[PDB]
Amino acid sequence: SMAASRRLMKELEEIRKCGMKNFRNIQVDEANLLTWQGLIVPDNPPYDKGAFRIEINFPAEYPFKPPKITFKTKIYHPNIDEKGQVKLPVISAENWKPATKTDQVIQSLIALVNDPQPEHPLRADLAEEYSKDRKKFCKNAEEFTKKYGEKR
Amino acid sequence: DYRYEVLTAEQILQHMVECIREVNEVIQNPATITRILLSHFNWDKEKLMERYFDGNLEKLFAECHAQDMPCQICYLNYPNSYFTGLECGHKFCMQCWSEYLTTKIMEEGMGQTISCPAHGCDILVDDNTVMRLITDSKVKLKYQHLITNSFVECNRLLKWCPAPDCHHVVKVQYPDAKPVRCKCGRQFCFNCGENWHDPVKCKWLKKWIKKCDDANTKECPKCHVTIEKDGGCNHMVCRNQNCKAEFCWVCLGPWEPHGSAWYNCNRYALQRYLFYCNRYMNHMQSLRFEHKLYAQVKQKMEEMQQHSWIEVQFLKKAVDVLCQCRATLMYTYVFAFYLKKNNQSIIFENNQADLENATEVLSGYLERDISQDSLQDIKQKVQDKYRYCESRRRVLLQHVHEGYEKDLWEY
Ligand SMILES: [Zn+2]
Ligand SMILES: [Zn+2]
Ligand SMILES: [Zn+2]
Ligand SMILES: [Zn+2]
Ligand SMILES: [Zn+2]
Ligand SMILES: [Zn+2]
Image 1 (cartoon, rainbow over the protein chains, first blue to last red):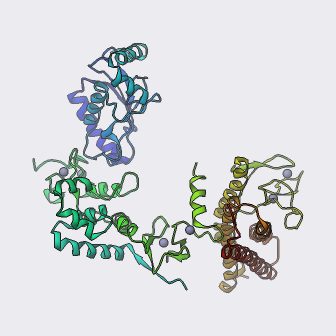
Image 2: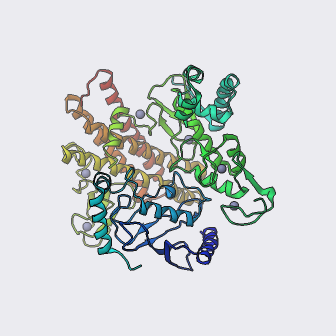
Image 3: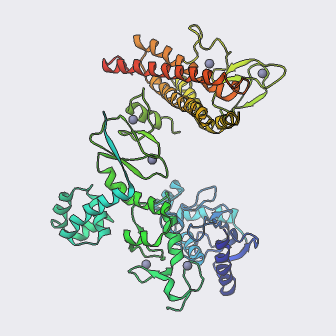
């Protein structure tokens, strides 16, 4: 729980110093350091008309266990359920590598946002919509994004 | 007799390593890959050779599966001396290895190989350098367990001890569904692997664990004051001034028409399951509180020592009888739930009730009534009680077994 904070300290120092364009507005509780927040700003439609609140949650055993990203803003995406949990492969307990950086983890979340992977989804019905009728899904997700998004 | 032998995960590894290195001199692979190969072919050294030349190995192998820098996991700087690596050339501090390995060998997502901690790469860490980098023999044991599990599953005369941190194997001359005993103490059924379950057959227990996989407190029948259960005994006396009446916790009817020929609450299709599951689960929950009696009795056995260790033995025996009986009892409710009612079942149900009552009486003396009693009187009382509890239990099991010898039981 302490060694995590010590590492996140160095990670978080390198982030605010070099910058992340696609991931903005980083708020962390300095007592804890194990619970960040921020606002993703995607570049591709059907999400480039808005931004999304995520909360990262580093366990005590970080970096030997992965964090857990959950969206607080509602989103229409085959790989993120309604409660907010994301199925990001690089973060799962099977694939997680303790040398994987948080910046890489997040860049990878914006990969998923910008290119939905319907192959192993959380919303199975949204995955069908995406493949079988792209144009219509992109529009459904656009109006959900405009209705529940965040200012850039 | 039913002979068997207990081996440690250390010994059961030497067995495997020898079984490897007799294949590994023929095929000349590294020791760790041969293991994964042999595991994949269920330790048939033949169906491995009839594929390790037959086909192209690639399909086989596919079927089976900056120097003065800080450490890329912890970000601290050390002398190059402390950075170990794998064959990929990815290097990390010798503690991050130990921390990674260690947390990788704890249940959720373990297969039977661990790969390098680098981002991206999946070059496996060979068995022998896992042992070399992790320290504490507790963890080390677990790893041995995991790499040897295939080897022990594929062998029908070895089962692991079910106890969570014991990694020992029982080795038998034949499989039989008799009871074997680990040397950590744990007594289990060799055939099915679960805890010993005398009256019920293994099949019907499997069916009852799947079907059961998917109330802590309750209110007094008379005065309705919330009673949390603290102790396994079901003879509940009400902790109140208004109502000091007695009641069986399961059925919530009265004591003491319990322990008679007339009143029986142990005798009864999802309404039915709830009846039998309630009694099983209750007896199980009860058994946990029953185990924590080695404390309470040694407080009285210590207080009897000062007024020694010879006497302290009978109360342990008493608690060991009580636990075994509860355990039987638990399982007689599994056996009954699956039982087509027939001519023998009525006689069984009476024995079940005899054992149930004889348990509650022992269970409730060690929990309450011993301390409301003199010192010279309790050696006799407790002994007479557990000797009886033991007979009623032995009468019950004798009865079912007779029936099994003649196929009396239907389902
Ligand atoms: Zn390190
Ligand atoms: Zn590597
Ligand atoms: Zn054991
Ligand atoms: Zn069994
Ligand atoms: Zn009452
Ligand atoms: Zn009752």
